Image (tube, coloured by chain):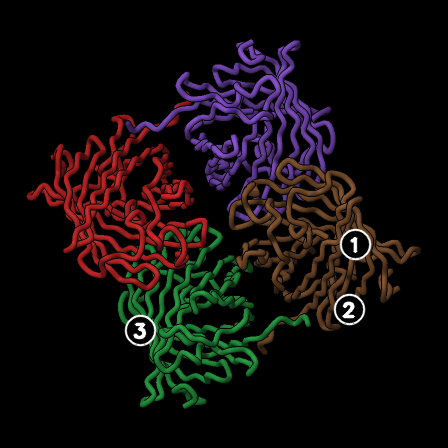
Chain colours: A purple, B brown, C green, D red
Amino acid sequence: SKHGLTKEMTMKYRMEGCVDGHKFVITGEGIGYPFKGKQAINLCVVEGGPLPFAEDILSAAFNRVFTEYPQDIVDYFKNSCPAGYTWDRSFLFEDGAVCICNADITVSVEENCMYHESKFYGVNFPADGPVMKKMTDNWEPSCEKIIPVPKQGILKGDVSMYLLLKDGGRLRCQFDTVYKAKSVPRKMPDWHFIQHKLTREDRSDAKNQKWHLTEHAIASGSALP
Amino acid sequence: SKHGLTKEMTMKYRMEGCVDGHKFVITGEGIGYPFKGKQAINLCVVEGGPLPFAEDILSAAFNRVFTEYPQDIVDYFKNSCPAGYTWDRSFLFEDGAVCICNADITVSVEENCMYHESKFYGVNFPADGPVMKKMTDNWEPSCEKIIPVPKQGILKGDVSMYLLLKDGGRLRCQFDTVYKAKSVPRKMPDWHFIQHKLTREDRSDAKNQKWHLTEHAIASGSALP
Amino acid sequence: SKHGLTKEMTMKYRMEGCVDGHKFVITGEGIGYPFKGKQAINLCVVEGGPLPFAEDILSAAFNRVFTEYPQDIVDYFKNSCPAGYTWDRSFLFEDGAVCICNADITVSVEENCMYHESKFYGVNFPADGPVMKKMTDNWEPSCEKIIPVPKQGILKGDVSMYLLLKDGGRLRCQFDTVYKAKSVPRKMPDWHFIQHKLTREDRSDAKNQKWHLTEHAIASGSALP
Amino acid sequence: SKHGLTKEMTMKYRMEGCVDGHKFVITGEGIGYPFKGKQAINLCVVEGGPLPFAEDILSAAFNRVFTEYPQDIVDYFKNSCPAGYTWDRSFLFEDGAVCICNADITVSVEENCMYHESKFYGVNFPADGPVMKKMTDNWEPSCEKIIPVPKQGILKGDVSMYLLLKDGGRLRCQFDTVYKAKSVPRKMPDWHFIQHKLTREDRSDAKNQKWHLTEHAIASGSALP
């Protein structure tokens, strides 16, 4: 337990949200590899299912503890463990839709388990758009810039996202995040990138709306010397 | 009781919110004149006070029932009473801050009272900005365009807002709203304007953070023949 | 000649531009009523015709001298005559397309003629969008907010525009303008609105791409006392 | 002459522009290494100097031929040579300022020289902002996403930029580009990244406003397998 963390951990999730007036609760459980930047999780809609919107919008809402950091970049996220960190993000879609999500990440060292409590709110998705019509097909892999705010001991993230559409199109979404360790650290990173790759597969049956999500994320510095 | 409404009504409010990680509950009570488009209300912070942010951001969150409508424009809001309407709005500040608010408006005919339940979420207000530093000084009066979405029996509102700053500056904020009557009406308006004027005065003491808010709003069509 | 202006004036136009790599020159001539806020003009494509894009995008580019001002609001535009004023505007379409236009307005008192020299640049219009496919059908009437910048003796304009589409849709465009009298005046207005209504009719033949444009514009203050 | 290109080339530049009403012409000459993604150039203000704005805004305006491409990603830019390619870009600053630039890139094989003709237009830079006050201090290195538009044989670029400020601040700017080879190729790349690093040093004297610019750029695919 480097920071209360081990090589392979279990994860528990609860999300409450509201999108275009529709309320929901999702729970989840998963397995992850903090130092590899890999996680796989299983989500289950527990109230308000079946959702009237693409599962895909919730993907980036379901933990930067799961990022592979080179030893030469300060790992702000693992350093915040076990107590953890919280994050706030706005999603600005190019069609005017707007989301906000807040999460709180925390470790139980005794259970070797990461807990994740989030709130997801979305307004203004066009009723006829690919989100509300569930015609999306995963996010394209990305490169997020992580920026230190040194007077405050917090980080900003900035990633321009593309949700691939079943019909061959792409829907742009701007992510702006604020990452806050529960204790503001004296050790801060310089700006760096984190690259991400998601997969998402619906596994819904007659009882429940269910799906499987994975992320692979790797932090790095500029490629220019 | 035209639509469960009388010339002068009382109003009750409850808001739960979260801004930059700070949770709060506000209650309120007021008096309003539906057909004059006038209302005055008194807000009281009931949890999480004193707020770390300008009271002003909550202003447009605290009821288009209070708008003076000419007889020649369909009044979508009064027509939705007594059951009422819900609305969803994103606030896009020019400094990257983002808010979402959801309200539900409903009439008790027996009490001659309008009830207002809202949720306010805000993320990314710069810690050193006039909002988090409480250096704001009311919104400038505005002209909002109301746009019918005829396939859906809902309205959009679009208003470009300016929060005046104590130091002589102005902070831009883009409001985009979706207004939904609980029953989608057959009678719909054409696009029109609603002009608004707010006043806000802090009345805080040692016991409580408290303030007084008023709105005057008037609907109209284009001035060009 | 109040400010070199008479009740009815003629107007001459020249525009050079470039949209998605396509260069053009348009000339025009018209008649206008400065104090009524009315103008009608005839445009003629002189190089690079037929244009590959909707005539409609050029509409707001083709003179705030033509606005009806109440005596109680300073008329910054007529006050700048005969020398005139220049203006700069960005057009931000919701599909990512971006335009810039610059105009210079000047009066010849001897000819009772207003001259208008402009530059129009547009990039990123999707090749398959209603602009490049010429499937637009005029702008919806608007309400622009005019804001004084008192340290500088210039004005800002802010109008949220809607280009109606032949198929029943609407394309949003954000106009942000800076208006600069060639001499910065001591007399400045308070913020006010200017409402606008355009008409546009193609009158193209075998020789030339030609069309007729009109504007009616009226300035006013807030409707709330 | 792989595509009319050699390992080390000279470059000639001409730019005409207009920023906040101020017109200028800049010329330049440089040396570059197409296959290394390196270039260094010397700019000289030939009309309208000294410029009233930061040299830094012109930096990304002064040739994706200078990018190091791995053999396994199609190099759209070198493949377009010697005839070349054109590009169009909007710059959206967070304070509302807006620029557009258009360039045309072409090779003279006989002279082993790349020619670069551009137009730069900027409107709405606040007179008191770090750009108009010349208080900027270079761009932070970036990661631009390059996206193929396969029906059209063109590319899009998307990069979120940060202009560092002399006072320790940062000013955000959104770059959106369209890259067009003069012949639309059958060979197209998949989406990839290009990382960039600029340096800029003023070398102005009594005769002329002059400066030295360098870029290093390297293309790559996602780091996730």
Hey, which residue is sitting farthest left in the picture?
D110
> Badge 1 local density, few (<14 within 10 Å), some, or many (20+)?
many
* Residue A131 coordinates in the image, percent (x, y): 58, 40
Q: Which amino acid, by three-letter code, is at mark 2? A: Lys
Q: Amino acid at mark 3?
A: Arg
In the rendered image, the quadrant that contains the N terminus of chain A is top right
Give the x, y percent position of residue A23. 72, 37
* Rendering quarter of residue B162: bottom right
Mark yes or no: residue B161 visible. no
Badge 1: chain ID: B
Report if the CB atoms under discs 1 and 2 are less than 8 Å apart: no
Above-or-below relation of A74 to D116: above
Q: The disc numbered 3 marks a residue on which chain?
A: C
Residue shown at 33% from the left, 69% from the top: C118
Q: Determine the CA span between mark 1 and mark 3.
A: 57 Å
Residue type at mark 1? Asn
Indicate whether C106 appears above or below D51: below
* Residue A48 visible to the viewer: yes
Residue at image x 46%, y 83%?
C34
Element at label 2: loop
> In the image, is D9 to the left or to the right of B97?
left
> Mark 2 belongs to which subunit?
B
Q: List the single residue furthest toward the right.
A: B110
Observer-nearest residue: C56 or C88?
A: C88
Q: Mark on residue B36? A: 2
Mark 1 or mark 2, which is nearer to you? 1
A186 or A205: nearer the viewer: A186
Quickly name the residue at label 1. Answer: B42
Identify the residue shown where x is 12% and y is 38%. D9
Q: Position of residue D89 (x, y in %)?
A: 34, 49
Where does label 3 land, which residue? C14
Mark 2 or mark 1, which is nearer the start of the sequence? 2
